[PDB]
Image 1 (cartoon, chains in turn cyan, purple):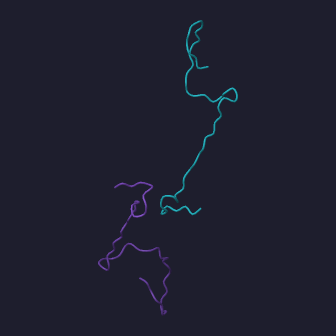
Image 2 (tube, one colour; image 1 turned 90 degrees about the vertical axis):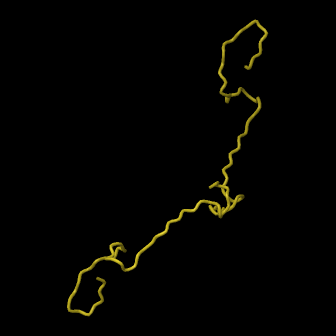
Length: 49
Length: 49
């Protein structure tokens, strides 16, 4: 490459990073920042296990 | 000013310094690092006093 500070746009260097995921192929080990709670039972509720 | 990294030439910042001298007005005190040497006598030489 010929990167120079005088080069116009379309020739200045660019840093690129790509992130690749999977969707439910195994017990997931990379979760979000959500915090767990207690565990209720014998009631009609919604869960996020 | 609107200095942005994507700006083309003719808009990027430039740093400028100008130097001004005087000529033959007083005993000079600022000049290059010439190596002062020994002095000889009774010989046809060129001097830089």
